[PDB]
Structure formats: C-alpha cells, structure tokens
Image (cartoon, rainbow over the protein chains, first blue to last red):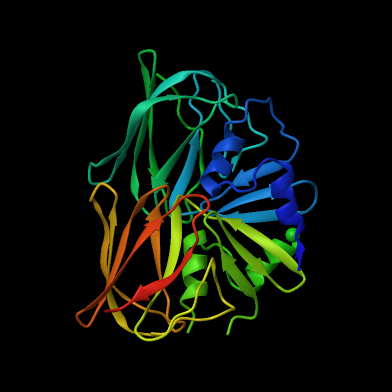
Length: 161
Length: 156
Ligand SMILES: [Cl-]
C-alpha cells in the first residue's frame, strides 16, 4: 500500500529507476571525497545501503563486482568494498587491466581509469577463479581472484613493482 | 535492519541474486506476499509497504502461449489473470532485429502457465514459441518502458 523507507531512500539519493549495476557504478565512481553522506558497501551478493542505523539490501545480478585499488607505497586491508568510505592511494590514474580465468580465457583486457576514490570496479562472471593483472607506467601487480559467493569484493593487495 | 531487509530474510530471498529471486517467485509450484515486475525492477509487497529491488543488466519478459482463450496483460505479477497452459513443453526462439538468434531453448511453462526469459536490454526483435507443430510469434522490445508480460501468443 505505501512506499517503504528503502524505496524512498533510493528516490532521494538519485538511485531510482537504475539497474543495480548502474547504482553500484554510480556510487563507486562518485567524484566526491569520502565519506559520502550515506554508507554503501558491497558483498558477493548484496549492495548494503544506510542513512543511519537502518540498513537496506539490494540483491546483485548475474555478475560479481570486484573493486580493486592498486598502490605504490602503502595499502589497507579490505574484505567487502566500502563504496562510500574508503580511499585508495591512486585516484584518477590510467591503468591497463587484464582478467584471465583458470582455463586461459581473457575476460577483461583494457585501459581503465581509477575513480576519485582510487578504485576500479569490474563486473565478472560468477564462480570463476583466475588472475587479475594491473599495469601502470612500466610497473605491474597481479593477484589470484575468485568470484564465488564467499569471495571478497575488495582487492587492495596490488603493489606495483 | 529495515522492513525491507527483514522481508527478504523472512521469506528466504536473502543472498539470492535478483534473477534467482524473480525465477523463484515466477516458478513457484501460494506465496504469502505480492510481487510485480517492471522493465527495471521487482516490486514486493506485504500489504502495508512496497519494496523495490532494481533488476540487473537483463530484461525479464514473461509470456503465456495459448490455444483457445487469452487475457490482456501489462506488467507480470502474481495476482491477476493467469496463463492457460501450465507445465507444458515449448520450444522458444528469440531473434533480434539484425537476425542474431538470442535464445533458442526448450522450456517448461510454470504452474501459472507462464515462461520467463532473460533478454539483453534495448533490443527489438521477434519471439517465436512452438508446441506440437503449432507456432506463435510476436514482435518484442526490451526498452526501459516495455511491458514485462506478453499474452498475445495464439498457437496455430
Ligand atoms: Cl524499508
């Protein structure tokens, strides 16, 4: 009969009518310093949103979201990515990004720009295992990744050497 | 925890992707809640409040082949007029405007007489359904304002 607080939250933060990917992309890529006015974190299966004590959960779709932040000097640990609170070391930098699965298939291969928050997000098939490689100005980092339901959505262990 | 998050947990929708939730609902063999799907979201209600779950990259189209009788339908929901041919085998083909075959599958209609397909967004094309040497066809589109229910499929 009446609009939920959850539905109203969506409407007031610019998120109504968007697909869940567009919502995640919009939030992760917002060109503001952190923290954002509301909290947002992402797991293998849910986007969690909050205006205060109260939490809304939006199911993800067919694709797993991995957000990673390459670094040169220092890093911080991360399991589920905070779209609203975390700052990576390298904002607005051009990277070359390659994701390859366990049987050699290239899933991602392109030039990507890190966001204001220093992260890059990719949308990946679920239940794969593979490798992410990142490269910047002659330097590279790589790390094993997986996209099962218990896999992390945040990868910060990418020291460029 | 919000009314919304609790609702999902309580009805065992927690940790499912939005496609799994839609599939579960549409394919159920008497859900204690209401549900309606649009081009861009799933609406859920407990009768007091309405929750909205954004869909993903694919459009959900639910359709009902028929032989003798049919009913008009805008967006697909649990309530309203149901389909006509429950738990039957069909062969479903979807071709896009440039002739690419998008789906070609044998699919079983659900207890409500519908079949659901997940399609790329912003495409136009044709849906064709076969059953016992009879066929039905209809133009379809998956734009942000297209309907998610198609009942105009007379098997002939
Ligand atoms: Cl709510």
